[PDB]
Structures are given as C-alpha cells and as structure tokens.
Image 1 (cartoon, rainbow, N blue to C red):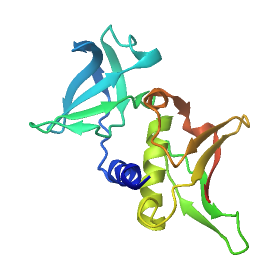
Image 2: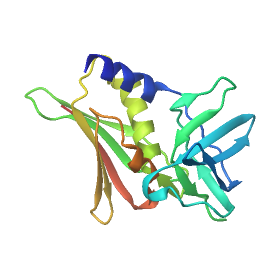
Image 3: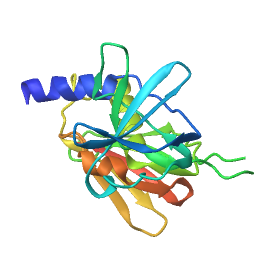
Image 4: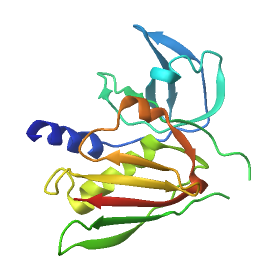
Length: 192
C-alpha cells in the first residue's frame, strides 16, 4: 500500500554487494546464527534463518554471498539474510538467459527484451529477485509509477519454475534458495 510500496522501493533500490570465496563459521547473535566476515573494507553479518539456521557450524570454505542490507549499522556493517552459494569451480562461465518484461492484460500492451548476464555457476533466488526488481524500478518505474501488481517467473529447463509476486518483498526463507544458473531457461516478468 502507500507506505508498503515506499518500503519496497527503498529496499529494492539499495546498493548490493557480492563478496566472494569466503571462509567462515557461524556464531550466535542474540539467538540468531550469523556469518561474520569482512572483504574490501566492508563488514558483513549474514543471518541464517529457517531451514538453514544450523547450516555452517563447521568452518566452511569457498562461499559466495549476495548481500542486501536489512539494516546498516552505526559502524557501516551490512546485516543481510541468506544469499549464500558455492563459488564457481575452476575452469570461463557466464549464463545469459532471456529476460522479457511485458504487459499482456490489456488491449494496448508491450513486450521488451532485456540483457541479463549471470556470472555465477550457482545463484541464489535472492540475487535474481533483487537485480530484476532493481531494473524494473529504474527502467519501468516499479513502485514509483508502475503498479506493484505483477510477477517474475524464472523458468527452469526442467520446466520447473520460481514465481515471485512483485506486490510483496521476497520472504526471508526464500532468500536461501539456490539454483544452477545454466538451468534457467528464461525469465518472464508480467506487469499487470
């Protein structure tokens, strides 16, 4: 609604971070398990919730993290949820699934291709959701002009798919889901 959409716009407009090849072990943070680490002067605090709550008790190596802040602290720390993937195994890798943004629920509509590259062999749904929404905000004025009624559909070569409702923020639990980027057949966004 009025305040909820301003929230979406602020959240999905924020700057993201992609620290890579991280070695870390989970620690307690007032009852939540988190991954504390630094890279390129930024300090990160990645929360582990739900099914992944107890997932990195042993020191784990070679992790990549897509971070979006839920809060930035008074010292600049980035508190993010999920976004943990396994780094690319030694090799070149770039996926380039088609991405169409369309309005098809009226007489006068549109359909437009966008160029989307994914440089990780394993990518989080969190990342796809964030980057696509950011593009929808800047190019299509999502949450500032364009209605929040719509969806992002990521179709897998399996024919399975991941659907994201634009009218709500991705749930924290889905911020842990991961997939092989080469298995993404296409991505379709419907702006209703």
